[PDB]
Amino acid sequence: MEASPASGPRHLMDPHIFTSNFNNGIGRHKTYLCYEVERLDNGTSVKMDQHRGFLHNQAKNLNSGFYGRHAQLRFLDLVPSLQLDPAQIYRVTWFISWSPCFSWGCAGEVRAFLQENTHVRLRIFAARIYDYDPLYKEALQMLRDAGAQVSIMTYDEFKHCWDTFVDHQGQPFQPWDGLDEHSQALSGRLRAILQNQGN
Amino acid sequence: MEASPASGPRHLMDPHIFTSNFNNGIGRHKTYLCYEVERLDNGTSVKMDQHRGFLHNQAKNLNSGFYGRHAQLRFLDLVPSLQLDPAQIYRVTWFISWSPCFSWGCAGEVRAFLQENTHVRLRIFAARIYDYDPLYKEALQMLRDAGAQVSIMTYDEFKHCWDTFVDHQGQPFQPWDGLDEHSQALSGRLRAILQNQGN
DNA sequence: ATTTTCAATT
DNA sequence: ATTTTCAATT
Ligand SMILES: [Zn+2]
Ligand SMILES: [Zn+2]
């Protein structure tokens, strides 16, 4: 019986949208970013505060003049709020529909954050391939330089995130047989990007 | 602090979604429902760690067996979970953008729920009143019979609720100049229903 | 004083 | 199997 903590508002994420994004369909222009924080204890992962939530890529607000090209940047401002202790190592993983992105501030701020805080491990799950202009391959190399942690989402991860972020009673998440074929096609691109290391 | 505790899941709704729902436009579905429970203690209001929450129409899916049901029905099942005791008095207030609603089971169950638990005070707030001509008049009369408590929320309540569910720090809510005109409309519409009592 | 959005089948 | 590619105003 897994369920999300009741300490937060019963604002569960619309399950239809969660499955719609991972419906294995083509089309994503405003998905969401899911992130989690864990505290390591002598090599043992411990979820003390356990911070779990999601962010919207759409950044509207002309009155505030706040804009966010990618939800990853918004989460960076959330790290300071948590005030993580540099003397301790925390495992933070980001779940976004697309992993690669173009933006000096994104990779620049993200790379600087890892360099300023090497005691933090950043894991990013690539559900889709965001290529774009040629700088697409270079963008991953610049980000992968500090975030050399890229992995394709798996069924077990989807079920965990579904029950963790989505609370359904008597209605279990039903997996579709398409991750093996989709992971293979996307996996081919993932290895091709790293192959650029040879030349 | 005024901001909701961060120890709970950040799965809170972003200010863009909250502002979009408060758009107060003409349409249907996507209804937003917010509810709050307070525990009275010897005449002293006391709130638990965090039992606040909200529900929405979300998406549909007949193929998955999804049925169109009012969020109020799901909330009623949440009352039992709280295991409220009749020896204590609890103040539960539901915030709905629209007042009109089909008595599929909310009005019918609500009338029975109040009769089964008269030691519970239920307040109903109608942010907007415009959906039907005959059902709307009857809807208020049916709810008024057991929920003879109808009040409108002011801008101050919106600001408190905005930061309550919105995860914004240092970013005050910017209200639009339209509540004053709407207050007169709702005030005139609300008293219009009571005027039927005179004749 | 009123006006506008999101969303849904085969 | 796929050509999808994170932003916004009023
Ligand atoms: Zn980015
Ligand atoms: Zn109803």
Image (tube, coloured by chain):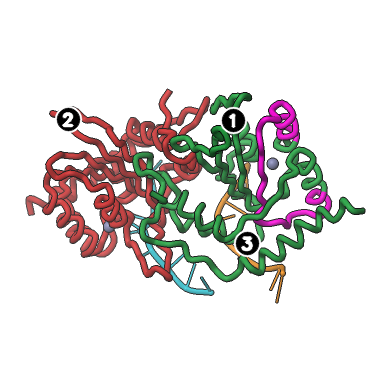
Chain colours: A red, B green, C orange, D cyan
**Chain at tag 3:** B
* Residue B97, placed above or below residue C5: above
Which residues fall within the magenta stretch? Answer: B108-137
**Chain at tag 1:** B
**N-term-proximal mark, 1 vs 3:** 3
Position of residue B118 measured from the top left corner of the image (x, y, whole percent): 71, 30
Disc 2 residue type (three-letter): Asp
- Please state, as top left, top right, bottom left or bottom right, where the C terminus of chain A lies in the image: bottom left
Residue sitting farthest toward the front: B42
Disc 3 residue type (three-letter): Gly
Q: Is residue B148 left or right of residue A174?
A: right
Report whether mark 2 lies on the same chain as mark 1. no
Between marks 1 and 3, how big is the CA–CA gap? Answer: 31 Å
Residue at 35% from the left image edge and 65% from the top image edge: A67
Quarter of the rendered image showing ligand 1? bottom left
- Please state, as top left, top right, bottom left or bottom right, where the N terminus of chain A lies in the image: top left
Report whether mark 1 lies on the same chain as mark 3. yes
Q: Is residue B174 left or right of residue B72?
A: left
Between marks 3 and 2, how big is the CA–CA gap? Answer: 51 Å
Position of residue B34 measured from the top left corner of the image (x, y, whole percent): 57, 45
User: Secondary structure under badge 2?
Assistant: strand
Residue at 78% from the left image edge and 46% from the top image edge: B139
**Chain at tag 2:** A
Q: Quadrant of residue A140?
A: bottom left
User: Secondary structure under badge 3?
Assistant: loop
Crowding near pointer 1: few (<14 within 10 Å), some, many (20+)? few
Q: Nearer the viewer, residue B71 or B84?
A: B84
Residue position marked by numbered label 2 in the rendering: A41
Residue position marked by numbered label 3 in the rendering: B25
Residue position marked by numbered label 1 in the rendering: B79
Position of residue B18 measured from the top left corner of the image (x, y, whole percent): 50, 55
